[PDB]
Amino acid sequence: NKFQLGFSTLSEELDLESLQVKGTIPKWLSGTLIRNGPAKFEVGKEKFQHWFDGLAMLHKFSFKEGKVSYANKFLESKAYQSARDTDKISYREFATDPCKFTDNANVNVTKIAERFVAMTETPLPVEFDINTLKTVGVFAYDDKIESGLTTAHPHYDFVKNELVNYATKISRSSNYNVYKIADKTNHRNLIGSIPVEEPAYMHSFAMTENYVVLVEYPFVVKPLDLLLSGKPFIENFSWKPENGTRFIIVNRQNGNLVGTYKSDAFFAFHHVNAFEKQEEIFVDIIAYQDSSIVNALYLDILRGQKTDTIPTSHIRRYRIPLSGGQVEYEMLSSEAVELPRINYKQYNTKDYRFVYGISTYSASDFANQLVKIDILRKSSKIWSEKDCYPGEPVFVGAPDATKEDEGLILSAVLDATNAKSFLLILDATTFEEVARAEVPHHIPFGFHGNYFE
Ligand SMILES: [Co+2]
């Protein structure tokens, strides 16, 4: 297919002070954008089976007075170092086993204890230096919380200055362990433990003012299958729609169980935003009908001539009545959307109007548009370019902004005909280009990135 290059290895690592810039990047952009994703899809004659298995590479876009610098290095995880030095896959990935959890932290990046960390879904992040992109090593937590599975989608409370996440202890007495990390510590405080027979794959979760909401899609594993089966991690998970989806609501200041509520079965990788209003919670999710999208992101499908087989996801607003009752939803947009982002700093946990994402609607091609959904005016704005495949749109608010959509969108875009990627900068209000920075190579299709001031 045309986008095949986005799922092919990038072996080139370089450090460049200036990229060729078209347009003008506002003077006030003084921070660094870090992109994480897979960038090596084979090790000698052995191939990684899934998109999620590729060995983590970081991309650094640092903004100084209208100019932009770029650096990219592979994360020197034990997974990477072992593959490089033995030419054997040596750690168990999401969907590939070799012929000890992987530290292939290829999903996201954040800061814990004032240190930059790469994250996957195994228990421990991997610390890296933002200046050099060199790997420091395993970032240990300083606590007794047991876990075998977690998210690379921590929430952050700006008022209390706390990271919030959960970790699942997978055993014959499995538990969802909801925790927080105060600034300037790597000690996790256990907020609450919810016991569970068959843990669900919950890639992300919802946070409100007072709550963590775990949305437990009925895509679940038998602990003993995970311990004993010869099969890669994700193959041990089963779709059981007869369970329905369970919404688990935990007070995230005192760990009190607010309640559990059930809707009809659905699956999701990514939450958009959630908020309390009266005695109700609204949870906005990028929802699929079932878990089949997981099998659709195997590389042989992504690289193949049947990509219209890849199921679409849409923004569903679930309404949880705390007073009690079945959880119903409505669609916020008819657009197929993935990789959702918001004005997180100002609107996470709050009523809001604007979602940014990639279009998966297949009007003209696979994942070829950026979209901005106006939830209020049930409308959308679109960016696209012949033979271009744009990555996750990262919002950056402007200084002393008075509006939710006053700022910039940053997206790593693959130009398939040019066989090279560019950073695209849109004004968030108009959703039109203000600048782009050329990169001398292709940036493989990634997952998540964050802007650090
Ligand atoms: Co994700």
Image (tube, rainbow, N blue to C red):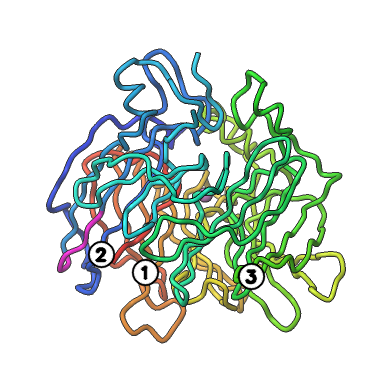
Range drawn in magenta: 61-66
Q: Which mark is residue 396?
A: 1
How far across and down, in percent of the image, does residue 452 sit? 31, 62
Residue 24 coordinates in the image, percent (x, y): 21, 67
Answer above or below: position of 265 versus 294. below
Q: Which residue is mark 3?
A: 254
Residue 153's tag is none
Q: CA distance from mark 1 to mark 3?
A: 32 Å
- Amino acid at pointer 2: Gly
Farthest left residue in view:
17
Which label sits in the foreground, 1 or 3? 3
Amino acid of disc 1: Val
**Magenta stretch holds residue 11:** no
For the point 47% across and 24% down, which residue is it? 48
Residue depicted at 55% across the width and 68% down the height: 373
Mark 1 residue crowding within 10 angstroms, few (<14) / some (14–19) / many (20+): many
Name which quarter of the figure residue 15 lies in.
Answer: top left
- Report the amino acid beneath label 3: Asn
Mark 3 in CB contact with mark 2 (< 8 angstroms): no
Vertical placement of 113 versus 219: above or below? Answer: below
